[PDB]
RNA sequence: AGAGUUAAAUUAUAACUAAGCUGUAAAAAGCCCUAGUUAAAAUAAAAUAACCCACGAAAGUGACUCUAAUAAUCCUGACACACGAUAGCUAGGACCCAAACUGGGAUUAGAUACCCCACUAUGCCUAGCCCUAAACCCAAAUAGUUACAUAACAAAACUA
């Protein structure tokens, strides 16, 4: 509002394909959480409720992170087995 | 150097700027301050539009004043810069050269946490 | 071909024109896309309104005007009324998160109008006023 | 990097107050979950709307606009072919990853030890 | 007679120090299509992929040059009492035994 | 705890332009002194950082600046002393926005509810009260050990 206009959350379209520009914008906003934030501010969410969410999210993230880590570590051993029909 | 005065002055011509800086520093020495140095960070377009003294401002001159002052007086100087119509926006910070840098020895890596659960066999 | 996603700052020498105009001189298409309705207003660079079209203006009624189709129809209409007053290129400003966002944009293109830049200015409070309570107690 | 687990859970030893309250214990399971099937949305809606405008304008005589009819048809054919042929390849190829069956087998070959 | 300690102290595996980034010599004892099972003499074999350049020169019995990363691939995962062994070693296949 | 300050929103209020705007699973009622854009004090609340885990005795505390400042050469200890979320009370001031209550609209067999719209006490500031919470990490304080050793579940078992 007091900032200069058009410098922010702005994407310029290339070779006239708009769908792509918009996609890029939406990716920018998804990445910075602006989208989730917008969506979550439609209604209010009482502090305890928010505390609970943050905690659940962080648990969830820890688990996904670690499972992923174990996948990428175990990934080598998916290769065809040498010892078949031993 | 003890306090740092961040001055954003209305953008003006040479003589009037010089005048504003002079009267400002004088006020500082009257609240009992000892002025170490005067730095000029130039005039720029302000990051956003700043409304002060029934004026909506776009550009501004930037200055730093390092000075020592009795703890009591920061409120006084603050009051003074408040009502000067040539100042776009004043601030007084504990001088960043007083705080000294401790040594990051490095990043101590944190091991995954163990024994959060018992040895139960599900 | 060097193509910057970032717009052309005013103080810059930067030379790009669309029909001979600077990036600053191009008209603005404001689009407010809200959950029950989508509104569009094309305006001069100098902020004189050229054209206005909404899903209500387009003769849909209560729930139907929520949908994407409606939004698109408003887009086309807006662009017609706009090209009448002779605006070839327009910079989109999308305000709000709704069912009609994308649709009203590509309706602006469908309706024979050229979109150069598409900006999102959605109110995001940095915590001002408390929004209304949650549904289903 | 994984978020820190130190000090987070409520335990007899921990000095401070809990940060996480996990709903179910944080122990890596020996299988992964099954991929969530994509929610569908209507297809061809744009071509439909264009054809409907063409009709409203020309008073619903089909001879008047053959292009939008034919293109709406073309599109519905591409949505049928899409529904048929995408099911199988989305159900097999995960790209850089493995089908959840293979992951589960791989994870049973090198399981987690909660016990001992 | 040589005390075990004396042997351990002089062995080439003690001489190496940390096994990260060490040039080593290894020998291929098993093959599945592109997979070379290489014994470099430590504990676990490693397994590398047959390179594109001179692919047919790599045969059971061949000798190759390796860059050792980790002597055993091991990690602890969330909720586990002990680490998990892949029962393998981590290496990069360089070329074959320039001689 | 004081004192000072404000970026993003929001609103009084004008200026253009449009007839609608709002609202839902869907409507109605409401508003058209309305809506979009451009300008804007006050008030209130503090995106991101935070995948951090700090401060405080606890309750609590995460916009910015400065001033003052975080007991004990550190065992336990009250009914004594001093504090203590929200709500609530008294008096004065504020009022953007939210909202018990209430009034309208739907829904329903009914609907003194859930859903929609308006609006109040109240949420804010000053001063005084009130002394309660699933004030729960349902795990007393201070030193310790990992020996013996599985009711079950849970956050492993124990000594003084
Ligand atoms: Mg309840
Ligand atoms: Mg503490
Ligand atoms: Mg539970
Ligand atoms: Mg503001
Ligand atoms: Mg007022
Ligand atoms: Mg009505
Ligand atoms: Mg903030
Ligand atoms: Mg102390
Ligand atoms: Mg005591
Ligand atoms: Mg109280
Ligand atoms: Mg109160
Ligand atoms: Mg009162
Ligand atoms: Mg009120
Ligand atoms: Mg309300
Ligand atoms: Mg009623
Ligand atoms: Mg006070
Ligand atoms: Mg509590
Ligand atoms: Mg109790
Ligand atoms: Mg006690």
Image (tube, grey):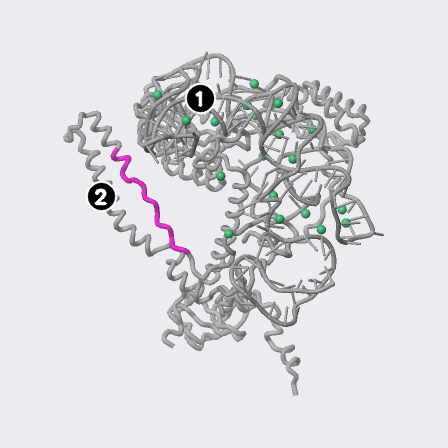
Mark 2 vs mark 1, CA separation in Å: 44 Å
| Residue E26, position as x, y percentages in the image | 50, 73
* Dominant secondary structure (helix, strand or loop) of the stretch shown in magenta: loop
Segment tinted magenta in the rendering: D33-48
Residue D38 within the magenta-colored segment of the rendering: yes
Q: Residue at x 40, y 39 (%)?
A: A23
Q: Nearer the viewer, mark 2 or mark 1?
A: 2
Task: Rate crowding at label 1 as few (under 14), some (14 to 19) or many (20 or more) other CA atoms within 10 Å.
Answer: some
**Quadrant of image for the C terminus of chain A:** bottom left
Q: Residue at x 36, y 36 (%)?
A: A17
| Residue C62, position as x, y percentages in the image | 33, 26
Q: Which quarter of the figure has residue F160?
A: bottom right
Examine the rendering and report whether any part of residue C124 can be seen.
yes
Residue designated by label 1: C45
| Residue B63, position as x, y percentages in the image | 69, 28
Q: Residue at x 30, y 25 (%)?
A: C60
Residue designated by label 2: D77
As rendered, which of F15 and E89 lies closer to the eye?
F15
């Amino acid at each position: 509002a007091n900032h200069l206009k058009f410098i922010a959350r702005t994407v310029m379209v290339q070779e006239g394909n708009v769908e792509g520009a918009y996609r890029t914008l939406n990716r920018i906003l998804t990445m910075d959480g602006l989208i989730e934030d917008i969506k979550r501010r439609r209604y209010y969410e009482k502090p305890c409720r928010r505390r609970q969410r943050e905690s659940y999210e962080t648990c969830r993230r820890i688990y996904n992170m670690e499972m992923a880590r174990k996948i990428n570590f175990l990934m080598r051993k998916n290769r065809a087995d040498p010892w078949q029909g031993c | 150097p003890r306090y740092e005065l961040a001055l954003i002055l209305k953008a003006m011509q040479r003589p009037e700027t010089a005048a504003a800086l002079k009267r400002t520093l004088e006020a500082l020495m009257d609240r009992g301050a000892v002025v170490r140095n005067l730095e000029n960070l130039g005039e720029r377009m302000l990051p956003y539009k700043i409304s002060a003294h029934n004026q909506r401002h776009s550009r501004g001159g930037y200055f730093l004043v390092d000075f020592y002052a009795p703890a009591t007086t920061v409120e006084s100087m603050m009051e003074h810069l408040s009502r000067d119509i040539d100042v776009i926006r004043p601030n007084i910070v504990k001088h960043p050269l007083t705080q000294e840098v401790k040594e990051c020895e490095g990043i101590v890596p944190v091991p995954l946490e163990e024994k959060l659960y018992s040895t139960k066999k599900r | 071909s060097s193509f910057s996603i970032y717009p052309p700052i005013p103080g810059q020498e930067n030379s790009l024109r669309w029909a001979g105009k600077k990036f600053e001189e191009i008209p603005i298409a404001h689009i407010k896309a809200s959950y029950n309705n989508t509104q569009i207003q094309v305006v001069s660079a100098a902020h004189q309104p050229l054209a206005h079209a909404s899903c209500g203006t387009e003769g849909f009624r209560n729930a139907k005007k929520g949908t994407g189709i409606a939004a698109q129809t408003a887009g086309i209409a807006a662009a017609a009324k706009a090209t009448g007053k002779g605006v070839t290129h327009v910079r989109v400003v999308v305000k709000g998160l709704g069912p009609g966002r994308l649709s009203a944009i590509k309706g602006l293109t469908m309706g024979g109008l050229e979109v150069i830049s598409i900006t999102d200015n959605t109110p995001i409070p940095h915590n001002g006023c408390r929004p209304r309570k949650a549904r289903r107690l | 990097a994984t978020p820190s687990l130190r000090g987070r859970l409520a335990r007899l030893g921990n000095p401070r107050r809990p940060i996480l309250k996990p709903n179910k214990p944080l122990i890596l399971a020996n299988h992964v979950g099954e991929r969530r099937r994509e929610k569908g949305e209507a297809t061809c809606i744009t071509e439909m709307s264009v054809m409907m405008a063409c009709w409203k304008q020309n008073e619903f005589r089909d001879e008047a606009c053959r292009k939008e009819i034919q293109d709406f048809f073309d599109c519905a054919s591409r949505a049928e072919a899409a529904r048929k042929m995408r099911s199988i390849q989305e159900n097999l190829g995960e790209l850089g990853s493995l089908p959840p069956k293979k992951l589960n087998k791989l994870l049973h070959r090198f399981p987690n030890k909660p016990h001992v | 007679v040589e005390s075990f300690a004396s042997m351990l102290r002089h062995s080439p595996l003690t001489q190496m120090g940390p096994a990260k980034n060490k040039l080593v010599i290894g020998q291929i004892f098993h093959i599945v299509e592109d997979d070379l099972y290489i014994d470099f003499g430590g504990k676990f074999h490693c397994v590398c992929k047959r390179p594109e350049v001179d692919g047919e020169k790599y045969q059971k019995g061949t000798r190759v040059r390796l860059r050792l990363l980790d002597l055993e691939l091991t990690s602890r995962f969330l909720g586990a009492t002990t680490d998990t062994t892949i029962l393998e070693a981590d290496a990069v296949l360089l070329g074959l035994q320039e001689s």
